[PDB]
Amino acid sequence: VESLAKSHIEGSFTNVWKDDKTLDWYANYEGILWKATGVVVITGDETQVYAIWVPVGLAIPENPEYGDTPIPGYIYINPLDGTYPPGTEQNPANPNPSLEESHPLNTFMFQGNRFRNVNGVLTVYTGTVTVNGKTYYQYTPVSSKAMYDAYWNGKFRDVAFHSGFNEDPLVAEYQGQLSYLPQPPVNAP
């Protein structure tokens, strides 16, 4: 079963999930765990992901009728891709993640990711982190150029500039650049 030196898969996978820390997408196929690389295209409902699936390890099972034509979707922006690294000349943003005791206010949802904008500085919700007995909420600086480009080009003007006591995240109108996922998924049962 140690066959994870497998050839990459360029295609769509169903039964995907996103890791709450790395914000990468994942799928189990042929008893192998795959990481979605290259240009990653996801359906609006996140049931399917199209990418260059790289084998990263052995499958974990704990973590629909299909056509043969391309289905609409969105180019997923992994906001932790490193194309615009924080704490650099290019990106002067503080490069350190914070541990919030509660979710910060006025955050927004984009591609199922939770973002906080503090005067042009973007941070992303990268899961909970239990520290000395309690649930903290980690917010990691955004290192994606495509994310900042969407922001700068006003693709979040509707959700990124709110102030006031607004605990629940708003949901952005813009959900990414439109693309297509080839069908059916490679791992269809």
Image (spheres, helix red, strand yellow):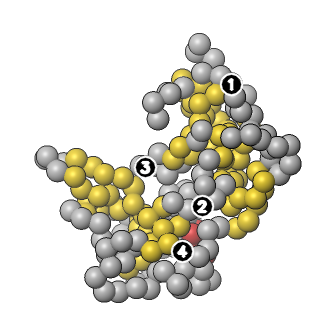
Q: Between tags 2 and 4, which lies in front? A: 4
Residue at the limit of the structure toward the left, as seen here: 132
Tell me how far mark 1 sits from mark 4, CA to CA.
38 Å
Callout 4, which amino acid? Ala
Is 136 placed above or below 17 here?
below
Badge 1 vs badge 3, beta-carbon distance below 8 Å = no
The answer, for residue 5, to whether it is visible in the render is no
What residue do we see at 24% from left, 56% from top?
A: 136
Earlier residue among tags 2 and 3: 3
- Residue under label 4, please give it: 172
- In 3D space, how far apart are the residues under numbered discs 2 and 4 (Cα atoms)? 14 Å
Q: Nearer the viewer, residue 20 or 85?
A: 20
Question: Disc 1 or 4, which lies upstream in sequence?
Answer: 1
How far is disc 1 from disc 2 in space, using C-alphas? 26 Å
N-terminal label among 1 and 3? 1
User: Farthest residue toward the front?
Assistant: 65
Mark 2: few/some/many CA within 10 Å (<14, 14-19, 20+): many
Q: Which residue is mark 1?
A: 6
In the picture, the disc for residue 20 is 3
- Quarter of the rendering containing residue 152: bottom right
- Judging from the image, what secondary structure is the residue with disc 1 in? loop
Q: Residue at x 48, y 61 (%)?
A: 113
Marked residue nearer the N-terminal end (1 or 2):
1
Distance between mark 2 and mark 3 Cα atoms: 14 Å
- Density class for disc 4 (Cα within 10 Å; few <14, some 14-19, many ≥20) is some
Position above or below: 85 against 148: above
Q: Quadrant of the C terminus?
A: top right
The quadrant where residue 96 appears: bottom left
Q: Residue at x 60, y 52 (%)?
A: 46
Q: Amino acid at mark 2?
A: Ile
